[PDB]
Amino acid sequence: KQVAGTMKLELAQYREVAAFAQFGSDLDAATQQLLSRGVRLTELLKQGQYSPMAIEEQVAVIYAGVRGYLDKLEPSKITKFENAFLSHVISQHQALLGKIRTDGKISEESDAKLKEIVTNFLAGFEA
Amino acid sequence: KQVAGTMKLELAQYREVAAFAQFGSDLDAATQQLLSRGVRLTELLKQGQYSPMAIEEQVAVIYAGVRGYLDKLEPSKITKFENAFLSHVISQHQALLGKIRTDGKISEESDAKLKEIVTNFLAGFEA
Amino acid sequence: VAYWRQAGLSYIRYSQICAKAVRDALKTEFKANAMKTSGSTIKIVKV
Amino acid sequence: ATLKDITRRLKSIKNIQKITKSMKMVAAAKYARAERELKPARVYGVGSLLIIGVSSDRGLCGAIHSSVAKQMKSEAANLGVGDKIRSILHRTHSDQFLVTFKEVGRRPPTFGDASVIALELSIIFNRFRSVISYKTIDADVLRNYQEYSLANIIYYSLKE
Amino acid sequence: DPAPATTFAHLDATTVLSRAIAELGIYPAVDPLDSTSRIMDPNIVGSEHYDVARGVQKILQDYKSLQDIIAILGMDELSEEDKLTVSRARKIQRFLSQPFQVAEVFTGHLGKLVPLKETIKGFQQILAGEYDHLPEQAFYMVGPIEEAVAKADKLAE
Amino acid sequence: DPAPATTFAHLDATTVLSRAIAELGIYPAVDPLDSTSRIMDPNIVGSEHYDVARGVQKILQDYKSLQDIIAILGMDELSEEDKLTVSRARKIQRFLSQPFQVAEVFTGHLGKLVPLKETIKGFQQILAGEYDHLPEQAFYMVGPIEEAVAKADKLA
Amino acid sequence: QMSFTFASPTQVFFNSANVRQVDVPTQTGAFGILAAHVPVLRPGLVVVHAEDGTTSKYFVSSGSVTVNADSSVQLLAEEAVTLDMLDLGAAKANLEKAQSELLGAADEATRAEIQIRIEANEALVKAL
Ligand SMILES: [Cl-]
Ligand code: NA
C-alpha cells in the first residue's frame, strides 16, 4: 500500500501523456519527469513466468522505481538492475526482507535501510 | 429573401475552405476574406433560447454580416455584441424597424441609417 | 585601426548600419523590397 | 472495428486531406517567390566562392531536417540554424553548442538573418535541384573581406 | 442500446460515464460533452455559472476535434491561439477529475468535497489563462483550485 | 468467424497466413505477430532462440504501431531512432520470406531449406545492426544470411 | 574586355558583361578598376563606364570587391540602388537624426553605431 499507493492512476496518465507527445516537441520539466518515471515503472512490472515472487520481494523492487532511484538510468537496463538488486537482497539482507514479511509493512527503520542499500547500489550500476 | 440568398452563398464558400482555417497562417487575401466573413456569419446564426425574433430584427442582424461591418470585430464577442445591439435598436430605433417591415427590404435610406448605428456601436463595444 | 572597431563592432555590423541607411533614404515607391528584405526574423537562443 | 470508431477516423482524415491539399498550395506559393529570388542570389553566392547546420522550424517536408542532422554527427564523430536542428540534434551533443536559432523557414530568409548568425561570436545545407529532388594586399583588408564573405556563405546556405 | 436509449427521456439530469476517460485515470470518468441537465439555464443557476459551463464544453469540444489532426501533423503546425486552447483544455480535463472518499482505496489520495463557489472560480481562472505558467499534472486529482497551486510548487522538487 | 475461431484451441502451433502480407510479395505470407507455438519457451528451445524470436517480434510490433503515421506522411517524417527500427524491421520482414521448392514455377528462384542454426544466426545479426548498411531487397527471397550479402554485392 | 559581374542579395545588374571601366569606392580612397589591373567597400558612388557612350550611375553601401589574375570582377553589395530611387530630402533628415543622436549618447558601443550611420548618410548627400 505504501510503495504502490498512487501507482495505478499515475501509470494511466503516463500512457495518456506518452501517447500525446509522440511528436518531438519541447516540454516542461514536470511532464518529462512523468515520462521518465512512467517508462521505468513499466519495466519493473515486466515479469517472467513459473517464478512467482513473495509480497516482501515485490515491495523491495517496487521501492527503487517509485522512490525515484531508477530515473537517471537507461530504460533498456532496468530489467538488468532489478535482477541484480533482487539477488543481492536475497543474499545478504534476509533480516530486512524477513522483517517486512513478519510485520507486513515498511517501518522507518526498514525505509532507512533500503535508502542506504539502493543509493550505494545505484552508484555501482551508473558507473 | 434579399439577405438570405447572399448569406447562403457566402457560407457555402466558407464551408469548403473552413477545414484549413486554423491550418493555414500564410493564406492569400481571397481565402482570408471567406474565412473571416464565414466565422462572423456563423456567429450570427447563434441564438438564445425562448426569445424568437420578428423578421425585421433578423434581417438587420444578417445584413450587418453580409455587407461586412463586423469583419474586424473579434469572433468570440459577436453573440454578446448582437444581444446588446438588438436591445439598442429595439429601444431607441423603433421607427427604423418600422421602415424595414413597411418597405419590404433594407432601402438606401435604411442602409445609411443602419451603417452609422453599427460602426459607432462596434468601436464602443470592443473597448 | 578604425573608429567603428575598437569599441567591439565588426564589419558585418558596419555593413548592416550602412545598408539600413540606404534603404531608409528612398522615395517610397521602391520600399516594397526594403520591407520584405533586411528582416530581423532570427531569434537568439542560448544555454 | 466499431461504427463509432470508423466514423471518427473519416471525420479527421477528411480534414487532413483538405489541410494537406492546402499546405502543398501554400508551399507552391512560397516556391514561386523562392524560385524568382534564387538566380539573383545564386550568381552572388557562386561569385563569392565549428559545424553549422541549416534548415527551418516547420516540419512535414520529408527528410529535409534529418538529412542535415545526419551529416552533422558524421562531421562531429570524426573531428544550429533552425528549431528542428535542436529538437533532433542537441541532447547527444549538449556541451558542444555556441548558438541555436528559432523563427526561420516560414518567411523568406533575408541577408539580415545571415548577419545576426555571424554577429553571435564548413556549413551544411540542402542545395536545390528540381521540384521533387534535393541534395545535402594589406593585413587588415583581408579581415573585413573575410567577415563579409562569411555573411555571403551563410546567406547562400539560407536561400538554397 | 435499446435499454439505456429509452432511459434518457425519463431523466431530468444525466451523468454519462465513459471507459475512454476512465482508461486515462480521469476519475470520476464523466463525459463532459455528453452529460446534461434541465436546470442548466441562466435563469435557474445564474449566467456566471452558465457561461463558464459552456466555456468548458467549448474548449473541450474544440480540443476533441484537434486531437486526431495534431496526432499525425504534429503540435508545431497549430496556431499560438490553438495550442493555448490545447494546453488549457488538458488542464481543464484534469481539474474535472476528483478524489472521492468512497474511492480512497483505489486512488491513494484523501477524499475532497469542493463547494459550488470554488468550482466555478476554479474553471473561470483556468479559462482566462491565470494558470498557463503552471504545469499540467498539478490539476490532476485535487479538490479545489488552491490545491493545484500548492501541488505545482511541490512538483518543482 | 466461428469456424476458424474455435479451431485455435485444438492446436499446439499456429501458422497464420495473411493476404496483406501476400500482396506485398512476402511468401510464404505468414503473420509473425499472429502466429504462435506452445514450445516457444526458453527452457525447450534454449534462451538464445527465445531472445532472438521475441526480439524480432518486438521490432516488428514497434514498426506496426507506427503504421498510422507512416501511411499518411511517410517514412521520412519519423525520427532517427524510429527510422532505424523501420529499416531493420523491413529488412527482417524480407528475410522472413523464403523461396519454396514447390513454388519454383511461381517465384523463379531455386528452392531453399535453411537449417535451424543459420535461421537464428541470420536474424540475430540483423537485430544487432550488422546489415544496416545493406539494402532491403537483398534479404527478399534468400535462404541463409550469406545469400543476403551475396545478393547485395551484385547490385552495387 | 573583362568578365564584369555586379549584384546584390535582392537584384542583379550585370553578369559577365563587356565593360570598359568600373569605378568603385573603398575604405582607402577609390580604385578605378580598368581591364588591366594587378591581383573592402565604403558608402559611395559606383560609376560604370559602358562600352558605347552612356555611363549609368549606381550607389553601394558596403561589402567587398575582387580583382583576379584573369580579367574577371564580382562587385558584392548588401544594398545596391540607382540615383533614380534615392531621396535627397529624407537623406538630409536622416543625417540630422544621426548627428542629433551623436550629441547626447555616451555609451562606447553606441557611438560607433551612430558614427557609421553619419558616414553612410553623408555619402548619399555627396551624390544627391
Ligand atoms: Cl451564477
Ligand atoms: Na519464411
Image: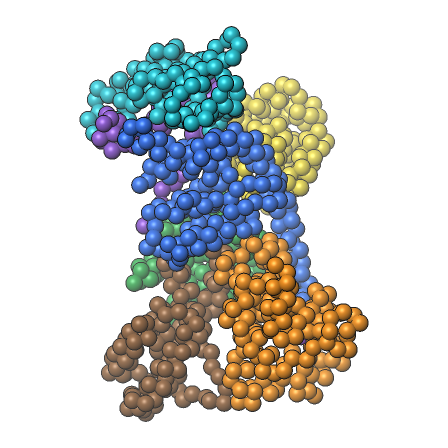
Chain colours: A brown, B yellow, C purple, D blue, E green, F orange, G cyan
Quadrant where the N terminus of chain F is found in the figure: bottom right
User: Can residue E39 be seen in the rendering of this structure?
Assistant: no
At a point 39% along the width and 48% down the height, the residue shown is D51
Q: Nearer the viewer, residue E108 or G19?
A: G19
User: Can residue F76 be seen in the rendering of this structure?
Assistant: yes
Q: Nearer the viewer, residue A22 or B15?
A: A22
**Which corner quadrant of the image does residue F154 belong to?**
bottom right
Q: Position of residue A52 (x, y in %)?
A: 46, 88
Indicate left or right for G35 with B52 as reference.
Answer: left
**Which corner quadrant of the image does residue A104 belong to?**
bottom left
Question: Where is B38 relative to F92, above or below?
Answer: above
Q: Position of residue B68 (x, y in %)?
A: 59, 29
Question: For the view shown, which residue lies furthest in the top direction?
Answer: G53
At a point 58% along the width and 84% down the height, the residue shown is F40
Q: Position of residue B98 (x, y in %)?
A: 64, 25
Question: Where is B79 relative to F84, above or below?
Answer: above
Q: Position of residue D21 (x, y in %)?
A: 64, 44
At a point 61% along the width and 83% down the height, the residue shown is F116
Within the displayed image, which quadrant is ligand 2 positioned in?
bottom right
At a point 40% along the width and 61% down the height, the residue shown is A32
Question: Where is A9 relative to E54, above or below?
Answer: below
